[PDB]
Amino acid sequence: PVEVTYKNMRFLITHNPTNATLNKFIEELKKYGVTTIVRVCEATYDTTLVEKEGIHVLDWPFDDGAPPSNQIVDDWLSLVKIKFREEPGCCIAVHSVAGLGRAPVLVALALIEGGMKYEDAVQFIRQKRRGAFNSKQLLYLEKYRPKMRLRF
Amino acid sequence: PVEVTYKNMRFLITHNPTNATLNKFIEELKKYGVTTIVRVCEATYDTTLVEKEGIHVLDWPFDDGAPPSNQIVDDWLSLVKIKFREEPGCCIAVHSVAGLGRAPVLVALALIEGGMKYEDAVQFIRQKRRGAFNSKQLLYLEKYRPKMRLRF
Amino acid sequence: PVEVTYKNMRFLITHNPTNATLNKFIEELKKYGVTTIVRVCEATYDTTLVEKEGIHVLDWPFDDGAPPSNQIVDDWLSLVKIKFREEPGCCIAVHSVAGLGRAPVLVALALIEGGMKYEDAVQFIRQKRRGAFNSKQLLYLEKYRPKMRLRF
């Protein structure tokens, strides 16, 4: 369970919780300023216990091996743009099952879209999630084309 | 006990030592290039054993919950400006009792005053001191207005 | 065994392996994207088992206490310039016996040559290799004069 940081952003990647992890998974989150968690992998637990905790749970699962939607990209970006400004020094926990694939991509995106070449972003994430990213994923980031409409 | 880094600065936040910690607390420090330690919380031990070690101990304690002086700010800034230039790659250990409040503020300051929006600085510190900073503290950083007279 | 990161670069400093470490030292490397390892300290093991692993082993040992060649500097720079572009998000493991001396210098170089004042680079490395660098080494970095021909 590692967290990154760029500019005013602070993402936390996580180990997909069980259904018995929760109460302590939320205690953990609760103490990371994580006011939002974007599920990317298939949901494997309630979100009521979470929601009833103040943590907003947005889940947009997608085929592990399939480039992360086209739409999702925009909700992420649109979400990211805001929050970090809405609540300064907060945090977005993005988690997938393994958290070395889709979870990083998402994060690796905001880090691009918000400046930083993709290489600088892959190195940056691997710096804190050794092994993260695979041939496909990489290929896809390389091919990603940012709008770069992010001003800080 | 975590250390940060920005530009040519390298701050180390610490767990307020006991009076039995010292000898090993200084061994630890001694091996961080820390040639100075600014006490922010109430002093709870001698400084002779420290001073007699080459580590300069400046202590400017202040009410935990009270914005860190107005003067202190300038001694910090004035101190920080220098040292990191005086002895390159050295270090300033700032410590308070908890080290999640005043200690960070001080540090979080130099990181502002030396560039970097405050959000970028809160995220940066929390990246390495999860939970650090509270409603008040934050509010105060937000309201801090830098001179920005720091050239690197 | 720590790794750093600047721009598109990702260096990993390592504990000089034994001759019984290998198989697991390569398993470790293998999982850091390290496709190259520049030996700076005297070689104390084969490189066949390594080479036969896809990891390119360049070794340019030099007197521990003697500024790192004059030529070596250029092979490093010339090597560094490339690879990180050749294979994005890869890694170069530089290792010496202690890995708090020559190994850092090498790394501390690319970080200079690729921008960043030397102070910013010493602090940056010590941030992740506390104690790294000595009076001499430092003196030498300070006196290093970059070409700064690195564009990212």
Image (cartoon, coloured by chain):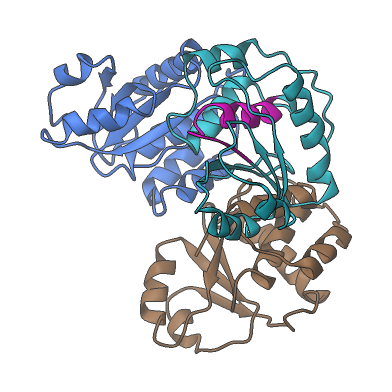
Chain colours: A cyan, B brown, C blue
Above or below for C12 versus B25: above
Residue C50 left/right relative to C2? left
Q: Nearer the viewer, residue C53 or C107?
A: C53
The residue under the point 52% across, 28% down is A123
Task: Kindly tell me whether residue B150 is visible in this rendering.
Answer: no
Q: Which of C75 and A53 is in front in this view?
A: A53
Residue A109 is covered by the magenta coloring: yes
Asked which quadrant contains residue C57, the reply is top left
On the image, the x and y values in percent for residue B57 come to 56, 78
Placement of the C terminus of chain C among the 4 image quadrants: top right
On the image, the x and y values in percent for residue C148 come to 58, 23
Residue A117 is covered by the magenta coloring: no
Total numbered labels: 0
Above or below for B76 versus B69: above
The residue under the point 54% across, 21% down is A64
Q: Nearer the viewer, residue C41 or B17?
A: B17
Above or below for B41 versus A124: below
Residue bounds of the magenta highlight: A94-112
On the image, the x and y values in percent for residue B62 come to 73, 82
Task: Kindly tell me whether residue C74 is visible in this rendering.
Answer: yes
Residue B4 left/right relative to B112? left
The residue under the point 83% across, 39% down is A82
On the image, the x and y values in percent for residue A3 come to 58, 45
The residue under the point 68% across, 18% down is A69
Above or below for B40 versus C149: below
Placement of the N terminus of chain C among the 4 image quadrants: top left
